[PDB]
Image 1 (cartoon, rainbow, N blue to C red):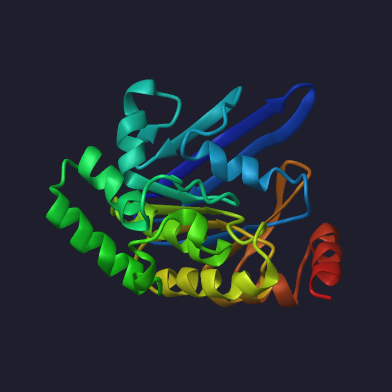
Image 2: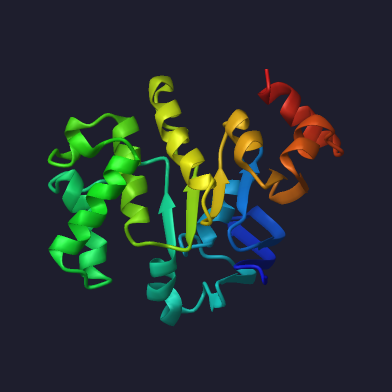
Length: 243
């Protein structure tokens, strides 16, 4: 019922630069929220404050009742929230399996037999079961990002954050990673996705948020936003991006 992510008057300064200018955003449980906008709109900054990767100077960011600014709540937030980025952040000297089993054994205190069985399932689900005994450097970006995805899912979070996970991928690698995201979007997970992929955005989102200049300019259903945009900034942005 209540929003699982509640953001009020979020202001973020990066030097003299006003990155976020009083964001009000509420994400419902299990909602698939997709955030789009031109570069420098602050959308990646916004999604990063949600699991404590950006400090903010004004406003309130609450995740499942936990204040993100509370140092006491950080460990708990890291259990509930998973995140993928442009960079894959894989441990080069750990196997694909070990990269995924690590946190559940270390944090959730799972035995090896239980963590690996879980990890292998997830690796299969994301299509790279045969990569389990390999080291990250032997994998392509498309494979590595899906390892990152499986690693996040292995902690069994209630919320999954996707900060442009295909933006640094070569074009051949994009499709395989988006498919995994589509698979997950049919489920009950609460998902926030920042992306350039508009086909994916209109296809999977329950709700699309258009950001520009550190503000939310327009939001709505994927059909409303892509076909009959209201704000001139929304319309202009889409027209160039949907080329």
